[PDB]
Image: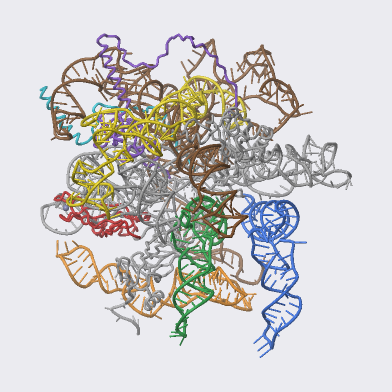
Chain colours: A cyan, B purple, C red, F green, G blue, H yellow, J orange, K brown
Amino acid sequence: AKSKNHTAHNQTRKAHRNGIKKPKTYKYPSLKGVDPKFRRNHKHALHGTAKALAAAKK
Amino acid sequence: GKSHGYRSRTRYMFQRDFRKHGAVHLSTYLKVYKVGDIVDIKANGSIQKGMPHKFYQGKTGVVYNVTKSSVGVIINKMVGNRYLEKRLNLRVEHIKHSKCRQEFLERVKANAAKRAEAKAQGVAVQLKRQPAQPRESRIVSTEGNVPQTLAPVPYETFI
Amino acid sequence: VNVPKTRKTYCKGKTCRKHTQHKVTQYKAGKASLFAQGKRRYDRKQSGFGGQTKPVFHKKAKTTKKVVLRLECVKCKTRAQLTLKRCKHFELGGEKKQKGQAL
Amino acid sequence: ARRPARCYRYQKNKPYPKSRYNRAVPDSKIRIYDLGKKKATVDEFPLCVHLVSNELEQLSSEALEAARICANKYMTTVSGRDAFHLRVRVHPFHVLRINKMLSCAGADRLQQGMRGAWGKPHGLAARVDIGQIIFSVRTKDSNKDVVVEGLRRARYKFPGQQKIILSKKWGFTNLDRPEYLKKREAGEVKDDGAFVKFLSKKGSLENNIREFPEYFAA
Amino acid sequence: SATYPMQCSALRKNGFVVIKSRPCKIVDMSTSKTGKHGHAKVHLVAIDIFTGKKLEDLSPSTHNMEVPVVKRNEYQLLDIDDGFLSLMNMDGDTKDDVKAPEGELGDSLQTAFDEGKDLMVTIISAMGEEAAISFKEAARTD
RNA sequence: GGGCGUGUGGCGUAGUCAGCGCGCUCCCUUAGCAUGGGAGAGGUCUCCGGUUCGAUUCCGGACUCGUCCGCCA
RNA sequence: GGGCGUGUGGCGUAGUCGAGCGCGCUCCCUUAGCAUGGGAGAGGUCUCCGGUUCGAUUCCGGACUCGUCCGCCA
RNA sequence: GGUUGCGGCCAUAUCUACCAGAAAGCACCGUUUCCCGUCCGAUCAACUGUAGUUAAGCUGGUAAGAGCCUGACCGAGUAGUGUAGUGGGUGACCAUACGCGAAACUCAGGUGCUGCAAUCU
RNA sequence: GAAGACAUUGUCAGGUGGGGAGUUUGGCUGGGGCGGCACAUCUGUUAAACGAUAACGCAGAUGUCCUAAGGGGGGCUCAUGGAGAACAGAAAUCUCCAGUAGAACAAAAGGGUAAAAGCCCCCUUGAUUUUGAUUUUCAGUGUGAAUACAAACCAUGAAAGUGUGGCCUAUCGAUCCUUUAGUCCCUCGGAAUUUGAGGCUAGAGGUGCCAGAAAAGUUACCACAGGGAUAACUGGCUUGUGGCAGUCAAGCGUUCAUAGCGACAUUGCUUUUUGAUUCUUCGAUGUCGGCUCUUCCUAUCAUACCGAAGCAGAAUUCGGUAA
RNA sequence: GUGAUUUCUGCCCAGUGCUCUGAAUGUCAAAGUGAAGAAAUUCAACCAAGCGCGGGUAAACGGCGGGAGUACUC
RNA sequence: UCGAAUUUGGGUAUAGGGGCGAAAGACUAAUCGAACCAUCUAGUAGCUGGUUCCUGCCGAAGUUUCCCUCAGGAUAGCAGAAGCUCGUAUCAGUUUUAUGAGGUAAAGCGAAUGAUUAGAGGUUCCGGGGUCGAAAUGACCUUGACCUAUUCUCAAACUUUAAAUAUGUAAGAAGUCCUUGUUACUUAAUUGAACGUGGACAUUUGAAUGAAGAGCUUUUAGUGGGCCAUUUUUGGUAAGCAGAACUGGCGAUGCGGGAUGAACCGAACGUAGAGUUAAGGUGCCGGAAUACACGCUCAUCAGACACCACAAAAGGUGUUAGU
Ligand SMILES: [Zn+2]
């Protein structure tokens, strides 16, 4: 009792029903996978920038 | 059985080329990548470390991470019915800058220059590109260009 | 394969925290103790009528085992394990390969 | 014991040459490809006649051998053994396979059917195209009527349709008759064993003068 | 490991098997279908290498049988005393743990050592027990 | 029909781009009871094709022999 | 029915295109038996028919004959 | 413009056979105490710039040169190919419509350009 | 009378025990069985120039090997060919020239590599520790393999740097249980000390039917649920094979291709052979052969009328209209 | 088990069974003995039958081969 | 077969894994390869059959991965429902421009690898056969190798070159430019890196076309046997055969045409009226020209329309038109 092995028939129709949406891009993407020596300094840089802006517009 | 390894069906894809084998030139090591650059991916078979997979050959992506000898690139891969985000760590021998991006930036700076110079007069800048318009009227003359009559040629064997 | 009897490697023994000298042995399993909880449960389950109550493995397929080296730091006596790939022949006695000599 | 040629007439498969993945083929039945006065010079035989296909099919090596023998026998009987030069311009490189089934009674008890039905080599064939020359003969202008009849007798051994075309070239070369005549009146041709070497304006002048002296003798 | 599994159909003649926890060497193999529908059964007739007894067995063909590791090793005699051979390895190692053979092989070896030939002894290892099977004489390097 | 092994001198087996043992034939020796030694001579490497200076051991294709299956309709 | 191979003196048997041996018995010699040996003999249309060659046991084609192998149904 | 040091592109730069090279620079070249390495101060190491030489390296030029590079309406809109027809043909296959468009071949031309620093009749 | 603290009896323990009990006795598959592994993987191709892509498609390979065949550095250039030198020749060692790799890099194949990734030499253990992220297979799970970093500690070199095993693509394994290493930390719940036991983090012992049951047969005495998803008739598609017919004509036929034949080739037809396939039928279409009886086909054995002959007659052969 | 009468029932005890009044440490349970420990416990020695070693048994299950020389012999 | 191992009445004994058997798996109340009765029991079934009113709106899948998985499930996909946040966009089975990537079709072999036909010129301390030679690393021919310049033909697992069709990215406001703040990162160094403050550039704000609203979430059904057509393509002699790729269909779908038919052509459907057509047709059946125009064909088996229901090689002073 052999049967059909594999096909890709109807698959693109199924995809293009409500399919091929591009992913939503955002301002400020995720920083995971970025180098830890860069992120460790970036935290302190933004902390100092926020403190300077708070002291400027306090 | 079947065989789907990591470098299956990559024979002509990862051959080097004709008469440019050997070591790689130093421009690929002297080129500088920053975060947000748009790069093309083309693997170098002479360098076995930091190789991309065969799917990403000829793919174009965006730099998100810069390390000592490699670059992190973001690709959008169609999986099923949507695109997924893929992060790749590739050595710099397998990437180069995309020239379309720098062409577009040249268009941006020349376009801003045109707008800046024509803002002093207000002459309807018309900064959008336009495609190939139909060609307009013209008068072609026969002075020294009298028409030559052509006819179909009869059949011959020609062997 | 052949592995030398000594090796300079890292020791996380809370006083070394560096590469020290290590003497290597091969890991032996040691005898299965009675009064381990699984052994007690197995004996209690096997007592009485009902026959064999747990599976016994038959379809053996491997011919080798992964070898495990027991490293022992010579300074502070702390021990480490590391495994190797599968090998049919293993020895710790160092008879070094020599190149330009006869068969 | 051989299948009819209609089972292998058409180019249905990819080319399957003898290689290091075949390693067991039968040898071809045609072995001689140039015959007649094959050692003749180039200007001995000005006229050239082609048997050329009009089909896209496969010609068997057995059919090539039979047509070669037929045309050679007819022309040597009517015109002499050394009045022509015949050349077979196709070579059987495609290998034909057979999935041999047993012809015994009650064969299905041991046949296994279409399982593992990859064939074994049994023959060799040459794949021709539209307007591809099978046979080419060069002779003098006094043997046109016998070489056309020889090719016409040879055409019966081939499947499909073939045409007999009298070429405009000089012999087995690729120049026209007046082009070759105006080339050979100068010394810029020089004979070889059967063919002829030509002069070019490129190359070193010393070699171009040790060869081909009569043209520079101007 | 000392021993490794194998399939009955993968086994063939002059190969080693484990039958009733004994190292055995096959002399006969025969496969007969169980029933017309069913798989064939393998009958195995083998001889123990150490003791010489004949041991047989019948199994399914797909069944897995245990197979020993047999190593044959070449040594030179030093002395035969008290029924224990003393042997000498290449690179100069010496063992005295081998017991002398007890049969006509042992008798022929004893007479050959008494009349003074240089004797080359083949001893086999399988499953932790050791014995000597054959001896020759060194034709050169006297 | 298919599958799996098979093939080297009188015999038996090993295997480097054909070796030993045993018979044989000689020679020498031992009273023996039994001998022993030294030399030989002997193989299309199953067969047929492509290579190579050396080819079993390089390669490919075929043959012989021994087995095992060829069932249920 | 088909395939593959085979065919030598009265018998067995050797044959690379240029019919030998052994056995039967013809004769002679030879024998204290419990009967041998030795020496000269006879013996083929190389299964038959055609072609090639210069000449086919030898090469080829056909026929005959013999020996193997595979084959009807539910 | 020549030469040296470090290069970029990596034959228009390579290869074969000849010819030429003022000045300077490279180079060959002289030496073995010291550092160092070899069977061998040949390579490598060190010393002198002295005893010499453009012979070679190197650079440039020559060749109906080989190769390589560029271009062509040269082959050729050819081969191939996306779309279409209730097109042809027993078939094999082939024409047409709307589009895209090669390679070999032939011919013509060319034979390194250049960045930084130093130095030169 | 006999026997006697031995038999017997009771409870445990070892052996024996198809006499009996319970159960099992893989999958894929041009039906099943035998065969094979297409069941976990790897290279090239099929594969139609992104990726993906099947068949019991083709050509092969894996369950290993390596303390160096890993890491770093230095020096050198290979296969082959030519020309030479006592023994020394086809092949021993030495010398020169040419040599884009035609060699080598553990193995299958494909890529990659020339002051090297090859050969030789020197020093070593980065084949180390701690957990994260990413790529392939993919559900964007696991496993395997791999990539780039961070924090240490090392190796090597003058140094820049390079190194988290093998130049790259294969070389392998969950829960439960046992055992080892670390923390010597947590718990044994009325309170302590010491054994013992149980936990936490990281390995090993293995499931190859490789996301991982503990497993022999027979049934012609057989049973049930189903299946035309699936074989054993007929019918249908195909016609290799079987049968029949052509075309061409090297030759046979004393001479002479075609009176009669006809090699090497090649074009067809038929479904009275056997295969191939699985479309219909498994809530059944009564599968040998013979007897009986009707009709149809023609590829004509005889009878009717003819043509041809290597047709003198006789006999015969080839062919036509003809069922 | 074989299946009246008559006439015979050959060879083989290696295997599988069956059977010994043989010989005796190889395998070797529980109880018991000894050592260590604070004890749970661990380790040894000793260790019945049966296996293992040694015999018998085919009117027990069964089995009854190859290569040479000249039926016979090796 | 009929004087006994005879036939038989009544009494009596043996009861279901049990009996009894001159042995057939026979008999044990029409039940026997384990009787009958009741209960457990409404035993389980991935398997077969059935499953009850109307209308409206939307509307599939036979595919991915894992499983003793292959007649079944889980998971993803396809679908419905409930909506939520917003109001013309952080869109698009499309094109253009710019820029990448690929190794198929083709082509090539006097280009590498491999196969391969034929001569020519050379090389013999450097071949083999003959003949002449005392012989000769002798000669003369011939034949083989190797080299040189040519020549004929090829490659799924060959390639310098190399399309068409498909395929990645970009075409701005989350942008560009100017100035200068932070840092424990980095640099010889306010050198750079990243994120910032303040300022300038607006409807041609950065190509075309269209937008039918755009984005987001939860939950759940059915499905997980497919099949056909054009083109590319694999195994096979082939098949209404088996297996793949892209698209369109049938399944799930009626209507007009192909006489007839799941898939072909045309066209997709609320209930009606009028008009015009598609594909197909207009002698009659049959609605519609026995229209018009130029030719060809006469068959003692004419021919008559794609899928499609067949015909070839070879021939013919039949006839027509050509070279
Ligand atoms: Zn330590």
- Residue at 60%, 23% (x, y): give it: B155
Q: How many marks?
A: 0
Q: Is residue G12 left or right of residue B129?
A: right
Q: Is residue D204 left or right of residue H9?
A: right
Q: Is residue J29 left or right of residue K29?
A: left
Residue D64, image quadrant? top right
Residue B27 visible, this angle: no
Residue G55, image quadrant? bottom right
Residue D75 locus on image (x, y percent): 68, 38
Residue D34 locus on image (x, y percent): 60, 40
Q: Nearer the viewer, residue K262 or D196?
A: D196
Q: Is residue J20 above or below residue D153?
A: below
Residue D154 locus on image (x, y percent): 66, 37
Residue B84 visible, this angle: yes
Q: Nearer the viewer, residue K139 or C11?
A: K139
Residue G17 locus on image (x, y percent): 66, 58
Q: Nearer the viewer, residue B42 or G14?
A: G14
